[PDB]
Length: 101
Image (cartoon, rainbow, N blue to C red):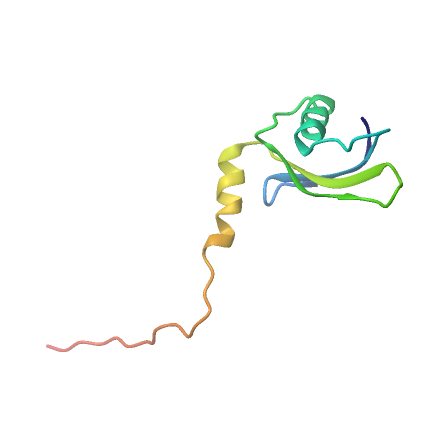
């Protein structure tokens, strides 16, 4: 298929990279893996570090778009994805301190 690098956003905070592009083809739709390998090859970056948010195929437009996430390290990708693993949904404890003697 054909890929077009729309824009490349940087994020040193999360340690990732928001890259946008458009996938074009003439027949059977491409596989996220195919696109990934393509991008990884395009950005000469690692696949493991390269991730795809979600591809969206148009209607009889022979074109699919999908945002990818390029990371500098996997260690980060883990911790980053480990941030949404610590969420609450209930009142916390309380508070109290003091002694004597």
